[PDB]
Every structure is written in C-alpha cells, then in structure tokens.
Length: 164
Ligand SMILES: [Cl-]
Ligand SMILES: [Cl-]
Ligand SMILES: [K+]
Image 1 (cartoon, rainbow, N blue to C red):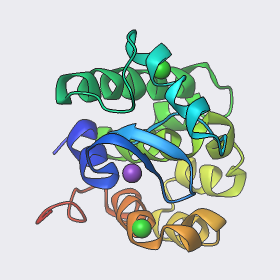
Image 2: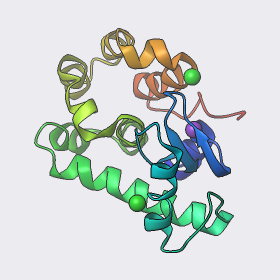
Image 3: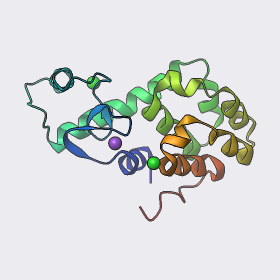
Image 4: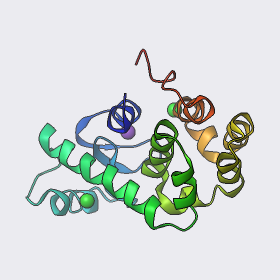
C-alpha cells in the first residue's frame, strides 16, 4: 500500500465527468474540476487541464496523469503551509500518507483549519487525535472514508485499506 493506492481506493476511477460526494463536477481519480453548477464550465476546466477538446471523457492514462499531478500538488501544498509542514515533518510515512489524503480531499486551507487535531497529532496522542478528527463535518459527510483515514492516523498501519 502507498498514497497512490490509498487514494485510488478512496476516490475510485471514472472516465467521464461525474459529480463527487459534494455534488461537484469531477473526473478520473477524484480530480475536482470546479465547484460551478455549470457542466459547460466543468467541461472547459477539463479541456484546459488535459490540453485538448475532450467532450467530457478522458483516457485512463490521462486520468492517471491528473492524479500524479494532484498527489504532487497536495504534498506541495502541505510543504508550503506553515500550519501543515511541521505536522507532516513530525509524522512517520504511513501517517504522512493519511495527511496527504485529507489535503487531496479538502485542500490545504481546509486541513490547516483542523488546529486541535493537528496539535494532538504532533503530540503523538493517537487515540485522542482520532476522537477529535471525528468531530467534524468531514467525518459526518464521508464517514467510511474518514474512518479509514483516522484509523491510519491512529495506528500508523494500513489495516483500514487492507482487504480493499
Ligand atoms: Cl489541473
Ligand atoms: Cl465515505
Ligand atoms: K470520487
């Protein structure tokens, strides 16, 4: 297991524009296109992102290319953020993937807002961090995914993803 495999499980793979859990146009492996309710806007983006006039469908290789970029951008965002960098630096590699996962799903700004959870993580109070992380809109809206990510932070193992 690794961050790519982890996120592939959590986000799935769809080759045509679809709506994510929040109702937002997305494609490939969780690549958010826009928060706009306009499909045309989403199609625009798709074309910009892939570099060609697509008509809302992409190939698997194209989906994987956006995913590679997206994982890299999440790591990049954590590293540039004053609130997240120290947390990321303090973690082991399995927990680092859990944080990248959160940032991919909600964005740098979003995760940096998790102040208290972040502090418990940096303190390495795993059980407490896990309880705290669950007290969130994130957990309530995507509880199965959240539980997976939280278990990863709690244990430092991939047990939540094995068998998937
Ligand atoms: Cl993009
Ligand atoms: Cl879920
Ligand atoms: K998805």
